Image (cartoon, rainbow over the protein chains, first blue to last red):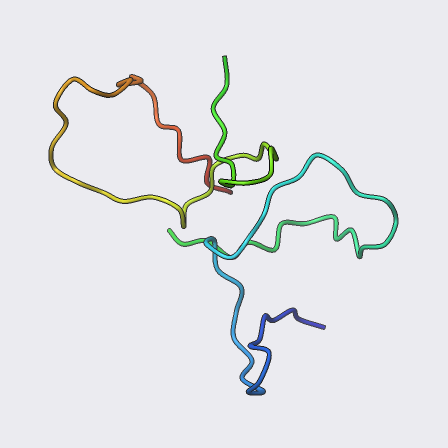
Length: 43
Length: 43
């Protein structure tokens, strides 16, 4: 149900942060397209 | 009008995120000094 980034060698699940993203003005149906934001920023 | 970071080899414009910044308590008039924040964080 949730979403997590991980390293390429160690299985270490962790919540996605704001500094591991790339914003692009294109998506071509090879994605997931969640209706809500999945950045998980802070208050 | 807008502002974008880019890589040093490929012309690929993209919005500036929160994890590509360095906060320093100094600026010496070799800057732009926008009155509004240009971090573009998320809700």
